[PDB]
Length: 110
Length: 48
Length: 121
Image (cartoon, rainbow over all chains, first blue to last red; front, side, top):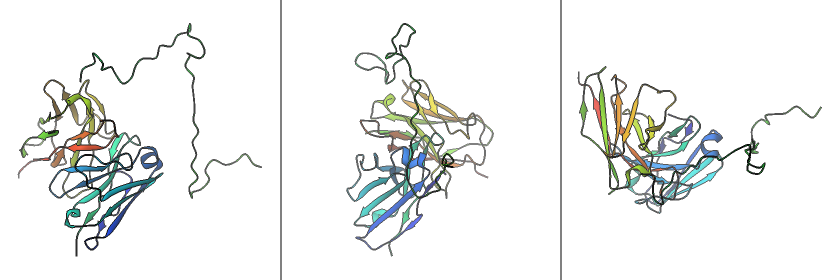
């Protein structure tokens, strides 16, 4: 586990907009662009955001990212039960020469 | 995956010689980068 | 379909050798970095390394240098993660990862599906 502070527990009604904040050292997020990931439980992870905003194939338009230097934000608008998964702020970084991962963001509905 | 026709290595070697001119010579460079966030102003002394 | 395929659920004994396989198919194989990542269950996401298959150039985890053995063969289209010695900390779900270098960034868009190596006692 690397120095990438992430809220481990999120919640909200279906249709809400969560904001996952991520911060750390400036060699992590200030240097390399922040990426965002999502892993469903007992499954494989998948990338959501690269280049601070851009998404790969298979990623919905609800997930949007922003980088303010060392700080970062993932906005996910219009929640449903698909967000029962831990979301990672990660990047390939040259801090300790690794694809450094975050603390997860697992959400449930109530 | 192979290096061949229309597919070269992303890095090529420096051709650097003493016969090369000063514009075609290697320079040692440093980029001091600062960012103003709320933190202790770190490297501080030349003022008194 | 671009996919890094790991095998089924693996059972071995500690201390011995084991070379986990990861087939690369559906894409130009030696055109992206292949990342081996660990997931011990109940933890935040762990990193082991990432390897270019053309010359086995691995950007390592500086705290596991020499412990984990990396290899990735081009013509077999397979990344191989080997440990000459197995332990109780190896018991984890490992994943592969494909980097989206197709005119983009350093994110890992395609992943391995996950394979647990265990010892039963």
